[PDB]
Length: 210
Length: 16
Ligand SMILES: CC[C@H](C)[C@H]1O[C@]2(CC[C@@H]1C)C[C@@H]1C[C@@H](C/C=C(\C)[C@@H](O[C@H]3C[C@H](OC)[C@@H](O[C@H]4C[C@H](OC)[C@@H](O)[C@H](C)O4)[C@H](C)O3)[C@@H](C)/C=C/C=C3\CO[C@@H]4[C@H](O)C(C)=C[C@@H](C(=O)O1)[C@]34O)O2
Image 1 (cartoon, rainbow over the protein chains, first blue to last red):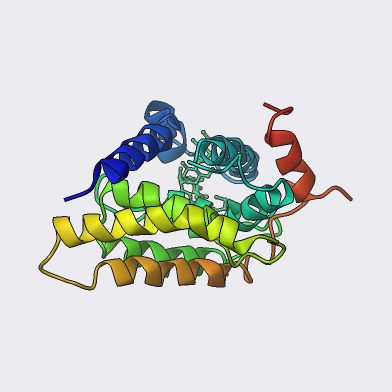
Image 2: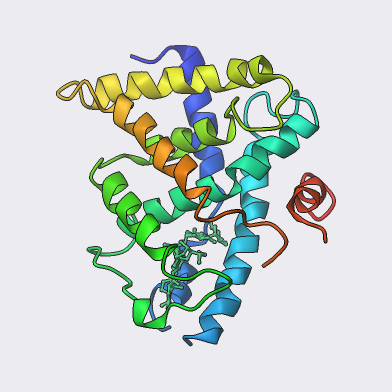
């Protein structure tokens, strides 16, 4: 039931959300873990190596470059963490055999990052999993998150809402197509962006490092 | 004393 405009936007997003791989040596991280203070050195990389993907994905979002310049910065400063939690969640249930559950905890350190990072990311994943959401839903739901016109430091909210709007519009349809049985699927997807905004306090901010 | 926002400025082209 999507319109040309939507199917076009969707494909574009899918495509882009895809050039970020390489699922093979996500096994180097999956099994056989050189653990402990080793494990730090890897994530710190991985993190870092998530920003460059994030920003590549964002530049190619229909209308992004056309935004202001600082607006562009403030978007991304606002999304970096949210969008990493959303990446994790896809992994934690879409990749990986049958969940429960990396369960390293008897190996959690700081960063500073302790045990109040573990628990958050847990409720969240299990709740996203509970949504049994397809990749298209991960892709769009991610652009919805970057293109958020209520980030602090935006000057042209309506410039950003014009861009977010169509993507919300598509996601609604997909929902209303792939699962008409439960007319409250879209509302749950939105609902989760809120647990995202929340974690933005317990992960005070990921500035500086590394 | 960077901190983040610079990183993003760079990543927007330079730091590739
Ligand atoms: C992640 C940093 C903080 C600490 C998070 O850590 C924890 C909890 C606290 C935060 C949530 C725990 C930590 C990682 C994350 C959860 C991460 C995932 C579930 C997955 O990764 C996500 C995020 C990752 O982001 C970098 C992202 O890849 C980035 C960079 C990639 O480059 C190419 C880029 O392709 C990609 C698109 O983008 C990735 C796609 O998907 C999963 C990959 C990570 C598993 C990590 C582990 C599994 O076992 C490992 C080890 O045996 C151990 C001891 C602990 C685990 C751990 O320590 O896991 C472990 O290292 O949560």
